[PDB]
Amino acid sequence: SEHCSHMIGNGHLKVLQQLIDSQMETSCQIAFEFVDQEQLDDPVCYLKKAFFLVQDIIDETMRFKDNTPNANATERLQELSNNLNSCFTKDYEEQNKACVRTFHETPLQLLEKIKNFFNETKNLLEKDWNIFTKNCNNSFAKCSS
Amino acid sequence: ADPSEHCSHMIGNGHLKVLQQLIDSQMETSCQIAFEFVDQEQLDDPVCYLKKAFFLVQDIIDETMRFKDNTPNANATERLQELSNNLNSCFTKDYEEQNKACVRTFHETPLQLLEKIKNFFNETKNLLEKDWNIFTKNCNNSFAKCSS
Amino acid sequence: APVIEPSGPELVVEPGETVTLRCVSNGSVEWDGPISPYWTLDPESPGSTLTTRNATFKNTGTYRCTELESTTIHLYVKDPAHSWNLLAQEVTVVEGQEAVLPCLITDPALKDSVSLMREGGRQVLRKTVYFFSPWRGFIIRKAKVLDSNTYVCKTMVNGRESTSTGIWLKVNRVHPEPPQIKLEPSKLVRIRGEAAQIVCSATNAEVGFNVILKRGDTKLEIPLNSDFQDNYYKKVRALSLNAVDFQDAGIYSCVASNDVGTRTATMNFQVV
Ligand SMILES: *[C@@H]1O[C@H](CO)[C@@H](O[C@H]2O[C@H](CO)[C@@H](O)[C@H](O)[C@H]2NC(C)=O)[C@H](O)[C@H]1NC(C)=O
Ligand SMILES: *[C@H]1O[C@H](CO)[C@@H](O[C@H]2O[C@H](CO)[C@@H](O)[C@H](O)[C@H]2NC(C)=O)[C@H](O)[C@H]1NC(C)=O
Image (cartoon, rainbow over all chains, first blue to last red; front, side, top):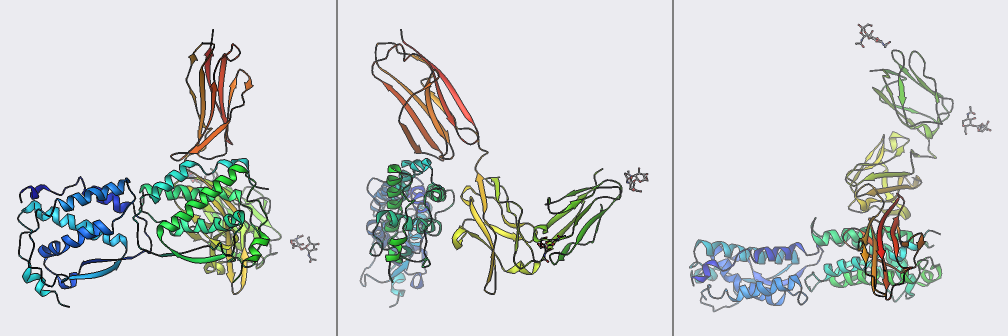
């Protein structure tokens, strides 16, 4: 998991911004599954619990027209996500849907939630690629209801 | 008599192209936003539909197409807002006490709203190319039919 | 600085009343004012004087007296039939510039029952940033091209509503110049008893302009092609030919023109 060190970068971080910068600000608000900070304080395990969800977001929600800049922007944004399994060590997953909650917010938000993920990720991984290798069972056990 | 021959060219494919790029850049979304428009179930005449839609479209552009300043979409929306202003010289006002006549509140997806805006400019463009005096039509009777 | 009579900051009178504005100052002075032909002048030794035997709402306005070689008073003529005194019906300005809509209110009391609108009782665009000035009318700072429109000044006081005529406002992103012209190719001999094309185009910020191509002093009949691109309209007249004669030869002219002027370009075509 060394190649993991230099995985995410700006070659796509900027691409995710032009994505956000291009969205119409409306009253629209969609539903989605993402981690609830109300029951997850550990930053190390936020990103961990979020990886899966994020990948879903990227695959289901982030849909753009084919062959459009934002489309391609997602394309890569996905490959990255896939080439990124090679750095998150699975944890003890009984009670699978623990720590996860449904969210009703503007795409504006959601996009952001995806923004900081690859951010805090491209951040911590630069500090040390072995991060994301931590054990989060103690963390997830804390998530109630 | 205010419309000129210049109306035949007020809307250019570049306006559409640019608007297409706006559309083509929005994320498909399970939404529903509110906005006022005409319900064809009440007003079906092609020309009068457009004449009634004109300000509604102006309004949409102004209050619903919000982008971050200096964004390419922000520019485009501003270029359209301009166009919608210029177009006024091409629609002759009509008469009606029930100003809100033939106008319903819609609940649709942002991409659908944008489609309406797109159909407006597209239809308006085609008709003005046929004849700039179009929209100089008396739509009194058509609006009077609108009910509820 | 000069001295004014009657004086102070703001003077309010009932219509019909007589009013004299005296500028007490050494020798010659001068009245910078929003007025004529509703006031009477008389620039003498002790200064100048402005007079009216019938103060009408049209007298509402700001008057300044300056040391000919520096003192201002604003007059409101409280008339209920008219809440507004229009100094002009059309204003022109440049992008980014301040734009005053000379809707001068005629009763300081109305100060809080004022509103800027578009025609038909429609509100002004959300992107329009403005505020009210009792002495100057509604104002738009950093006017954008999209602010260009016809506005009206309203005042609805307990059912009662008073609305000025329309003020036509025009904002330009740059000062208007005649459209730009391009003759492509700039010159050509493609003498053959045959094939040749000459494209004459023009650019302008607004649609109101025409473009024609000429051979000598004869205007050709070519279809028009139009579009909008970055922030401008383009119009082309493309001469297409399949077999050129000797009458096709000559000096061509691309001419374009709008409200401001005419721009012309010349090219030479030869075929021997
Ligand atoms: C108005 O009165 C003033 C002051 O009395 C005149 O200003 C002059 O004041 C002094 C008396 O004449 C002179 O010593 C100054 O040169 C002069 N002041 C200046 C420098 O301007 C003023 O001339 C009178 N107005 C006129 C032009 O008649
Ligand atoms: C100033 O204006 C008022 C109102 O317009 C004038 O009122 C007059 O209106 C007509 C125009 O002169 C006259 O026929 C009337 O004599 C008078 N109104 C009445 C019937 O009382 C007023 O006269 C004007 N001032 C002057 C000096 O003429």
